[PDB]
Image (cartoon, coloured by chain):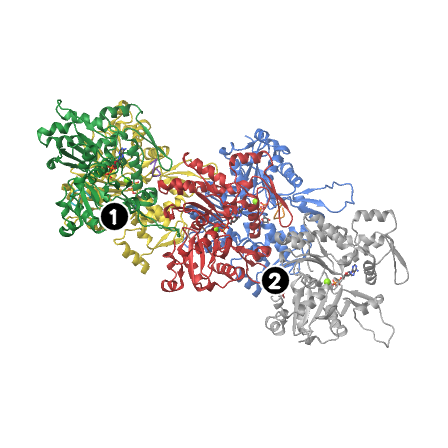
Chain colours: A red, B brown, C green, E yellow, F blue, G purple, H orange, I cyan
């Protein structure tokens, strides 16, 4: 009878809300900011840790830390602060009356899931809890039951194929290349035009530049020749203190790392080759059904050239008699949370919650038996 | 991670 | 007054329908498919066993098992599933109101027939039942009363001679070489050109290739020399995921195992020598009547070169003053069922049904006294 | 329960009073006068040192010495005389019953603060004491919590930026150009019109002329051309002995040294360039908040042309999309004392006094740990 | 009179030497390494391709490619580089004066053998050449004339039965599951403890871990319970850059894929069931002689638990009245080369070399008539 | 045949000479001095700009400007004056007969290199020219082919790892913290003892004090306690006008900013953490070879405590089983020029000069294709 | 292989 | 530099 | 079958 | 001050 909570804890953004809703109620950056100076003015309330948007509004006097990197929680006190700010200050609910659904990347360490279960049952003690895979939730929100999901967020880009409700665990692929690597590469290549960004607040500024101005080129060499020929692709951005910068080919050289990882010195293949290799590792008789149901999800897949480029690259890789379709819904930035809300509201899901007596009898190892 | 990342 | 049911349970295909009809109403592959993975998507109805065409449409996530091998039922729960799907989901009738006619290969174990009688009388309890020999049904569907029937299906190739309505039991021959062995041999010899097929769904793909593209050579050495000389016999096939393969001499090297069993390491003789030896073991005065009435039946005899080759081989074996005729009707893939419908609709057949009180009095051993 | 004392000891003026008040009770010039002649008249009381206004009323027979130069105490006996006159003759209180709050310029020698603590604890022994930064007190009296303070008095012109109650110690700038240098430059350039001032009383007369008649030009070259064209900017001043002098361009050539230090042979930049360089040495995300909160304090910033000139120069230096606001309250001559009275009356300030047992345990080095 | 050369070109290791010797002279990894960066230092000799051990010693700046996968040569220029390094840099001989013996897996494509014949006759032009089956060479090195050989290397695991010098070609089984699949599965399951290996040099590191620390459990469930109970099976390994990792049940979960292929999503049966099915496909009267002569060969069969586990599984599958013996010589990592040296030194083998005039007369198709 | 010129244009020192020599012939400070007063004495030759040592010998009447800040040329007329003084007055050669080799920091703006090429080809027009990376030249002068170079000069501290002649461009780190920041921090903290330095000549005096008297402490807290305990670390320096100053803990608080950048309000990490993070961003198999080949170069690394401190900090950061070696040659102040002389004298370097016809054909953009 | 592997 | 230094 | 097949 | 003022 009690409303469940869905909390997608990504590497760069935390999206929390109630099950049965269409959009997450609280979307805030998952950062913890700490002051690096001394407060000489007394009388007003100055804190030691700023969490979320309050860290972003005061980032000029704070050092910002991400508790999650590549989908792995590195700082657990900061993650506890993130969860406390999500439960009490944003959603404004008591966590002991609502079951909580959490998401996790595939091919992750087991200790991450075990400590997540232990913290959820001992610090914010819930009646029930569950850990789900994000690409399965993206396919849940897509409304279909078959397809291969490429989910790319802030730390993890992973491909998961599912045929008729059955997952293919040997064809699941994970690549540690996402939007934070693109932000770092943009910080590196912005020094060519004479712009220097070194701090964490400057990293947030470069992330805003990448979100506002970058796009995926259909043909990389033709766009590079066009940018070298005329200054028609140049765009201007206004810095917070008043300076105006101009960028040219760096609008499309930054998301080209998704298709050519060797720009940042990585031996792995691109996302199109990863998707093709994940398709070819499945059985033959389902492969055509995976060719026409490519589903995109996550904030990294929101560049305004990526669907046509993915279609062209997969059509080049695949045999010519197959139909290639890329499904890119406009709400794919929040599709993991939408699928979590669909899953937590199902009547058949109420029997696979991990309850408190099961955790009391089994310890923090029941999550390896009742989940993926 | 702990042996080939950092994280 | 009630309409009888005719159910031919072959090794690879199940053909069921009503007596008095011209064609069987339900023809489906006799396979049981089971999922080898875990269903991560909840909400929709996922079963544990897929029977028939539903096993074929979802074979990329299923392991497929044949309950019948070489005309012998090995798995009885799967055979019960096949019979339940044939009665309730395909024919859509109640089995307790209709007598049922079943077929069996000659020289079979007695326990197969006894357990068939026990299952038909105790699980799908019929008013009456009967077991017939498939070659006698092929001669019934041919419309003649004399001749030697070579029936070759998916597990059994058997020769039965009948003269003037009298069978010759000492001249009945059975050879365990049929279409599944040809499919396995094609799967073995397709690796020479660089194509690998190892799974059960790939076995179904190879069976489809064998059904579509194979043919029987009139002269094997001349056709091998022609295939080695020019690429005029090569044909192309499109795989389900889009690849195109090309085959050459394997179009006629695959059904040559029927005439040369030593290709698969078998000491037995070919089907032409088996037919000639079955003719030679009969009485002399009927032998000429068996020379002009060779009747072909079964799906294995549907290669488009087999009648001329069989005629040439038997004419080589027989003395030159005898006339050799091979009867190959175009409907011989279903001729056993047609003869079963002819036999079950006869007015003189109604007194040799095995009724339920006879089964209650004599147990599951009456079928050895009221049948062949 | 006892009322604290706030004593701003500037380089030219001493302002002392009680905490919680709006205006300082005792404002007197910090000079010590000594007679340079022989007293031939006997019977009345002639002293050896005249302190404060009594030094100003009898300055024609006295040599006047400033104990503080450039915010650094040079003569400690004269400074002790100034403090004794402030405590006993002006405020008329016993210093052993009241804690005392003192001010100090940034980037000062440590020995000045240590000897201040030693004298306040051993000669005028207080229950408690504290040393504060004058620009932080100006921001306290402004009522806001963010902004960059330019404090210019008699010896020190310093810029201190503070964002959200946090100081920026690496962006604090100090320039040794203030009103005494302007008085010396006016003393130098008054000889062009035929007026000679060489003594200390004549220096006080020139300081009075500078306070009464000088102003900051909006455009220097246009005002030079206007002064050279017509005698409309000329003003007359009456000397104490009856002579009347007239000055022209020297009304605005004297505070132009604040914007062009090369008039007195200094390599440093102007106050507008120092303010801009202090702004650009901070973080980027706070710079806009420092652009609209420029706070002026001190008696040197009381020229009636300086706010518009600083606004014009900073608007020329800053990018055009930023808003520049100069906050010039009319009570900014005493704003350091007002902020000291605000700080000393706070309930949260009572736990950071430097008490007498702490000085007894730690010696005269505790002030480097309990203060800035 | 000239000494013949024996060159076993496996999927992961190349073993070359002279006929008549006991051990191969040159054993090196069959990899080709290419630099993925730009050489900024000039003067010294940097090459474009590094072959063999030089690829292993400099693998941190190279991308490594295997020219052979699953016993099939995919890259022919890299294979030519491997053969050139084996002939000129390791053996240090001229290939035109020595006949060369090569090995090949059964059930291979014909184009592989034809292109090997063409390359050894046209690029490294030999007086004579021959292609042999590796399991026949393992039985040659075993010293016996009957038995069933299970050869498992880096790409192919194949069973070949031979009775009294006669091979059984219809009972030869090939399974594409070997040590590279075990290395990939170990990479996949090492992410559970928090160790990430994604590059090719990290693949070599994981292969070294698998060679040093893995073993075959006698009972899988009992060993899993023992590993879950106490940390007595945990072992530590030192990485090349100094980190120490610890592994538990992954020591025996990695070679369990040989007996349970469904760990990597493969429908095939284990090696014990493959051996039992290869035995049961032979004639009955020889089957007992195949039960006591199970010969192991290849580097994959060097786990220190595999002989007892194979004995237990085959004894469970076989009837209880038969004797099961597993022959595991200590030199079985090089037994294919030893049998090649035994075969090439025989006086009766000198008449079945494929000479250069026979290749000139018949083209690159003589190898299908003079070999297996 | 013509001798090449090597000119290292650092942020604080210009070192020019001939290729093939051991030491640079002309080492002079890269400053331009201009008079800030009026010359009342006529007859002798007074110039408008003083370049080099003549700027240092007459710095009491000049304002000194550095044309290069943080390895970026800001004033191009002053840089042209520096190059003219280097070519004509110091080296005394015609620049049109000698190719010239120049150095540049990594991660620099492209316009700096382009304008360097344009000025070298159009104002001091050379037959050929080249731009090199300074850390690669330091590794050239070290004589080895592998290692990670930490080069710290007057504006840039950068780490570049090179393995077997191959650079690692994604692991190159640049930090804008060098000796000029240390001079500014010493100027800031010298005000605590009562010494004021504000002008450019006083900045040169403070730089001389820092070069003569500063050292790197092995343990910062123990040395701070030792300096607070007794006056055994105090040292005396004589000013040019006769005053003697004494400094205590400021001898080691000034180069501690290299390890703790937060002393000057910088969010970056120290040089030891930058070196460790540059090592850990490389491949694993080369990391050991980067642990024993740490090469120091530049004048900032000439403090007499820095090698032991860097060894201790890296040994604390690295795993305990690795060997840490810091290579600190005594000639490392000029090692960039020595490596430039080694590189320009190589016979294999003569084919990668940027010639004048290539500049005429391609414009000032060829330097991005023929260099780093 | 070429149709059902890779290789 | 030009946007985040000075230089 | 059960003695020389399988089946 | 004591070394570059006076004061
Ligand atoms: N419009 C956009 N264009 C390109 N990238 C974007 C856009 N919006 C967000 N991103 C990137 O997507 C990431 C956030 O996506 P999301 O999947 O919500 O992250 P998380 O991993 O926290 O769930 C951010 O790192 C951001 O850089
Ligand atoms: N057109 C065809 N050409 C060659 N073989 C065929 C053809 N049609 C069916 N077959 C083979 O015949 C077998 C089915 O024949 P059928 O006698 O119906 O089987 P069952 O033994 O199940 O009765 C299948 O194994 C199939 O491979
Ligand atoms: N109206 C005025 N116009 C210009 N300058 C003034 C004015 N009033 C005071 N001053 C100058 O300001 C200085 C005193 O300012 P204040 O900050 O109170 O001094 P202190 O440094 O002692 O605190 C004096 O040197 C005086 O010359
Ligand atoms: N001691 C060992 N334990 C387990 N596996 C091993 C051992 N030694 C080698 N291997 C594996 O055996 C393979 C090499 O065996 P080998 O038969 O020589 O390969 P090839 O197929 O090249 O002939 C390698 O993939 C290696 O992983
Ligand atoms: N003995 C020394 N001890 C400490 N620092 C020094 C010493 N000698 C020179 N330096 C510093 O090193 C810098 C010059 O180093 P160098 O690498 O030659 O500069 P550039 O960047 O011009 O090449 C100067 O800023 C100087 O402060
Ligand atoms: Mg996400
Ligand atoms: Mg049949
Ligand atoms: Mg003041
Ligand atoms: Mg091998
Ligand atoms: Mg340098």
- C166 or F16: nearer the viewer: C166
- The answer to whether residue C80 is left or right of residue A333 is left
- Check if mark 2 and mark 1 are on a common chain: no
The verdict on label 1 being within 8 Å of ligand 2 is no
Residue A348 occupies quadrant: bottom left
Label 1 sits on a secondary structure element that is helix
Local packing at callout 1 (Cα closer than 10 Å; few below 14, some 14-19, many 20+) is: many
Disc 1 designates what residue? C95
- E13 or C107: nearer the viewer: C107
- Chain of the residue under the numbered disc 2 shown in the image: A
Give coordinates of residue E54: x percent, y percent: 38, 40
- Chain of the residue under the numbered disc 1 shown in the image: C
Give coordinates of residue E313: x percent, y percent: 22, 50
Q: Say the numbered circle drawn on residue A39.
A: 2
In which quadrant will I find the N terminus of chain E?
top left
Q: CA distance from mark 2 to mark 1?
A: 89 Å
Q: Nearer the viewer, mark 2 or mark 1?
A: 1
Q: Say the numbered circle drawn on residue F76.
A: none
Give coordinates of residue A201: x percent, y percent: 57, 52
Q: Say if mark 2 contacts mark 1, CB within 8 Å.
A: no
Local packing at callout 2 (Cα closer than 10 Å; few below 14, some 14-19, many 20+) is: some
Give coordinates of residue A35: x percent, y percent: 57, 59
């Amino acid at each position: 009878e009690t409303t469940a909570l869905v909390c997608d804890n990504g590497s760069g953004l935390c999206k929390a809300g109630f099950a049965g809703d269409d959009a997450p109620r609280a979307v805030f950056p998952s950062i913890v900011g700490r002051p690096c100076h001394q407060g000489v003015m007394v009388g007003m309330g100055q804190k030691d840790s700023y969490v979320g948007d309050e860290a972003q509004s005061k980032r000029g006097i704070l050092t910002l830390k991400y508790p999650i990197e590549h989908g792995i929680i590195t700082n657990w006190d900061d993650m506890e602060k993130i969860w406390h700010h999500s439960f009490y200050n944003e959603l404004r609910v008591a966590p002991e009356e609502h079951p909580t659904l959490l998401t996790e990347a595939p091919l992750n360490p087991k200790a991450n899931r075990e400590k997540m279960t232990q913290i959820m049952f001992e610090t914010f003690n819930v009646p029930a809890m569950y850990v789900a895979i994000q690409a399965v939730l993206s396919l849940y929100a897509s409304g279909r039951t078959t397809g291969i999901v490429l989910d790319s967020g802030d730390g993890v880009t992973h491909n998961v194929p599912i045929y008729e409700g059955y997952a293919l665990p040997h064809a699941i692929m994970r690549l540690d290349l996402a939007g934070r690597d693109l932000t770092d590469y943009l910080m590196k290549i912005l020094t060519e035009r004479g712009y220097s960004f070194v701090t964490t607040a400057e990293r947030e500024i470069v992330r805003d530049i990448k979100e506002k101005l970058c796009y995926v080129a259909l043909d990389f060499e033709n766009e590079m020749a066009t940018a070298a020929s005329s200054s028609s692709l140049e765009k201007s951005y206004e810095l917070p203190d008043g300076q105006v910068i101009t960028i040219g080919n760096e609008r499309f050289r930054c998301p080209e790392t998704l298709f050519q990882p060797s720009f940042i010195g990585m031996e792995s293949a691109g996302i199109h080759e990863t998707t093709y290799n994940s398709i070819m590792k499945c059985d033959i008789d389902i492969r055509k059904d995976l060719y026409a149901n490519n589903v995109l999800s996550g904030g990294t897949t929101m560049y305004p050239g990526i669907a046509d480029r993915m279609q062209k690259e997969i059509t080049a890789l695949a045999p010519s008699t197959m139909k290639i379709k890329i499904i890119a819904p406009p709400e794919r930035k929040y599709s993991v949370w939408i699928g979590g809300s669909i899953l937590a509201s199902l009547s058949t899901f109420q029997q696979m919650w991990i309850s408190k007596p099961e955790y009391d009898e089994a310890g923090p190892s029941i999550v390896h038996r009742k989940c993926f | 991670w702990x042996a080939x990342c950092p994280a």
